[PDB]
Image 1 (cartoon, rainbow over the protein chains, first blue to last red):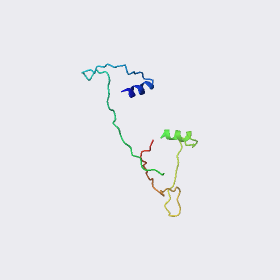
Image 2: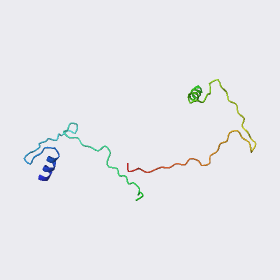
Image 3: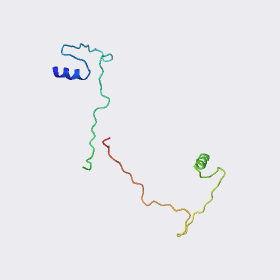
Image 4: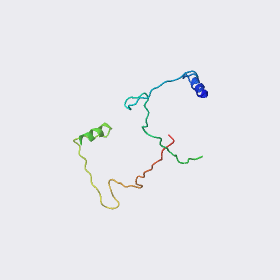
Length: 52
Length: 52
């Protein structure tokens, strides 16, 4: 949408409402365009209550 | 061992590898040469994870 386009543009990343991006996701997982994965998932830490 | 003697001499406590020290451990109640004892044995503390 337009708001995302404006926010991207103001962040020195160029993208216009008339632009399009074309991609191909490969079949074999060994060779791919973009690789994503989790090394260590989110771990919570609850610190004890402090003075004040 | 010789290495300990070398370390001692390095830190300004003169003790050659040739030197020998003699001592007498007393047994009478009121008299003694070297006194040792623990007033409070070592106590462990564990702190939880800081906000850092």
